[PDB]
Image (tube, rainbow over all chains, first blue to last red; front, side, top):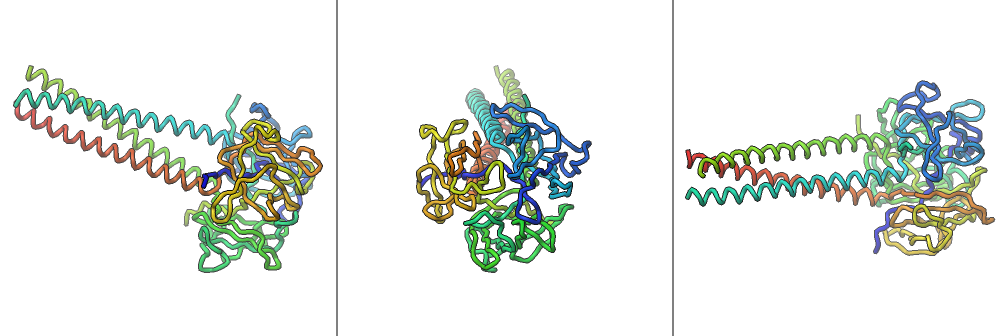
Length: 152
Length: 152
Length: 152
């Protein structure tokens, strides 16, 4: 057949209400240290827009949710990233809490390639070191054979 | 620049109809062994609410979907977990099948840290063992040099 | 307690408009090489329906989105896969661009088992090779002890 395990998916998040099927239109998102209350600025962590060229621009919290339920900045849809896993709290436009998640971690595709590069390197180092160890061993075995023959 | 590969996302699932843009309001979800029919109780696997403190309480199937398309128990939104990947079947409030997926596996963030801890330990064990092997080898090399000198 | 880190989730994607809370009804999706414009056929990559038995049938682009926001072929909901991470562009029924994502990578559960099998094998090979190296070393140590005793 063929091995094909990458699924066509929608990576752009949408945020909807908790009790009705509606977007959190003009809602607010706060992002903080895991297992903390991110509405408290002391718990907040840096958030960045990732631009199309892959650069990052730090922005202020809260994140804003549009009528589609999507995060926007300056009238445009944006992808927001952090360095680490994080807590999140979502509020609706009336200031009522929609949701709270203590620990959220979704990696974008760059993390997968970084990890794959790291793994590749690691395995090469171990295998290279094993091969070098075997070469040291076979040289020793040869020295031993020579000694044995020397002494009868 | 900065490396930031954690994307702000919405980890709370929503369940919607297959032919119209609507929540599966008062729908039902069944969870079972991979590649099985989970409506059959003999194929069902334990499901648990994961509470805010991280504890688990086993609950009965089906899981219930509210007007927002979100899983609820006892009038509150809940996160449901299983130990293993699983099949899932979704029915609407009229008893009509909405969807069936044979094999679903989404890990929450705790799995990532468990795996990272396991990896860290593993690599340390291999590297420690390599270093110990090299130390054994260099001691042997030294014994061999001494022998060589002894016998001319 | 119990370790349960598989979260009940909805793996079937839905595609919604960018400025209103609505499905991209009768929309179109194009899938291509990462960081390319997938509306250009020269940038497109093979897309396949993954059938219930796990087989694959290649289909033509664009992918079509129904009134629910879900991908359909021949009047039925389908799961679409590619071999590699990919770019994606979404258009609405009027030909207006809804979204563009340069690099999308979501693995279905089969990738996790392939990777787990590969990891298991790898670690077994390294550990087996370490054990064999130690056995070579202990045999050498024994030969050295014998030599030492022979020569005083």
